[PDB]
Length: 180
Length: 180
Length: 180
Ligand SMILES: Nc1ncnc2c1ncn2[C@@H]1O[C@H](COP(=O)(O)OP(=O)(O)OP(=O)(O)O)[C@@H](O)[C@H]1O
Ligand SMILES: Nc1ncnc2c1ncn2[C@@H]1O[C@H](COP(=O)(O)OP(=O)(O)OP(=O)(O)O)[C@@H](O)[C@H]1O
Ligand SMILES: Nc1ncnc2c1ncn2[C@@H]1O[C@H](COP(=O)(O)OP(=O)(O)OP(=O)(O)O)[C@@H](O)[C@H]1O
Ligand SMILES: [K+]
Ligand SMILES: [K+]
Ligand SMILES: [K+]
Ligand SMILES: [Mg+2]
Ligand SMILES: [Mg+2]
Ligand SMILES: [Mg+2]
Image (cartoon, each protein chain N blue to C red):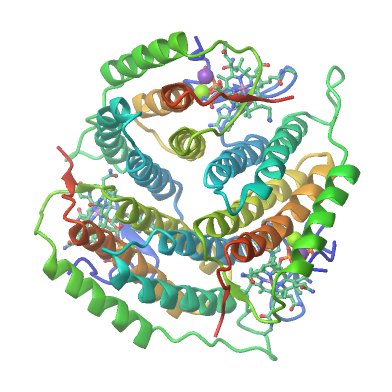
């Protein structure tokens, strides 16, 4: 049974031996990353023939978000479990995509209102849920030692979702609307 | 008029005579349950010919979430209003579904990335919004006496959404993807 | 490059010279408004031939939410930047729509469960995300001087989304379901 009932009184296990209240900032941080991961799954389910080129990288992001969650669930002083997430390669990978998608779409200097195609709009939702998760991670960092590589990656990831959302509109030739 | 303007300065009425700031943990708790309820409505709107068997129980969950919200909005010491939510029957009902859906889908021991069909992905989003609401309920419980039956049910409900999401993928023969 | 990396350590610039941690209540408040704005974009992407009459006003709301975010990002004592958002005209505009949509749909005295068509369900999600943003704005207001016009408008806006959701169901002749 996936239901153990052990969480019925409001406490839960993290990685290692510690238990925490479910509203503890650590649990909120990796919980928000799980919410983001689920939204990325939902976004991927909206891919169509015009936007197939985005499918594989969204799946890759889901794998990465699991790695980020793992590290957020791991206390820095846990002897039996180490941080596994290293920002450099995944973050450079995001930056290459951001560069490519920024270059290819029509240039703007004005704010774009988030929207357009259903997929582009979902990528803007991903952008903002990523940023909400990021706020939670910073709340955790102010109380506990974290793997700061996760913060670097999560920061860059919301720029990826912005750039990808504009690219998704481009792929269907849907214009972005500007803030008046 | 549904707009009374009484909330324009940031305070609002709960059940009974009390008013609270809108960011009070009580208001946040039943507000998050309302957000979950709206997401469940959205998820139900995605039902298709393959997944019709899930429609009625999602509606039932919406009725239950209203009952949970009511109790969260009710102070334990309110003389004129009592708790109405009793966990036993609805929670056993969820567990029977969890058992049936766990049994029928392909077995895994590895983490599944949340996604697949649009409905399954939406059920994973429901899973994570349920868990966010749960965190809020625990925040409330640490400051005020609550109907702990709501916490039991909300805990079990996110396991229901996990099991139902895998079942929704099964109903369309969409494989779950595993964490590498 | 849209990625400056300046946020990689958890601090960010608001309007004017101040930097704040990303979990600061000010950043959370306008961050939640950005999340709402993205959800409004997503909702607009669901418009169909039955519901085209709702498209333009959703776009207008997105423009207004940018104005609200701007003011939330602006300290009251910032000498170089002023509040731009004035509630009266946009709020009266919302109230006229609320009146018109309340009048036209079938009357109820009982709670409606949030759902129905995909668009109506998305408008209920908008309703609840608006209310979450509102809670964040009240958290900010309790610590800092804000443009209270934003709070007035955001309060009224969740009533707009309720009324519009019922109207979206009406436009497709989808009944609302009542709480038993
Ligand atoms: N509401 C929540 N939000 C975020 N993370 C959670 C929440 N509840 C539990 N967790 C984390 O996710 C893991 C899996 O959740 P799960 O629901 O199985 O835990 P539980 O609630 O403690 O147990 P059970 O649900 O079996 O009573 C937990 O071990 C914990 O790390
Ligand atoms: N932002 C919010 N988040 C969660 N719950 C809320 C919020 N605002 C109000 N509530 C709760 O939901 C009920 C209905 O909300 P409603 O918007 O009608 O209240 P209000 O904002 O106090 O009044 P009004 O909107 O008419 O000025 C309230 O009585 C209160 O219990
Ligand atoms: N996680 C967040 N949530 C909400 N608002 C944010 C967040 N991060 C930054 N902001 C606000 O949004 C604006 C744009 O965000 P952006 O990501 O460009 O900032 P940054 O993270 O400080 O910089 P960079 O991402 O280039 O390292 C910021 O100037 C700040 O006002
Ligand atoms: K469980
Ligand atoms: K109201
Ligand atoms: K940036
Ligand atoms: Mg950033
Ligand atoms: Mg649980
Ligand atoms: Mg209100």
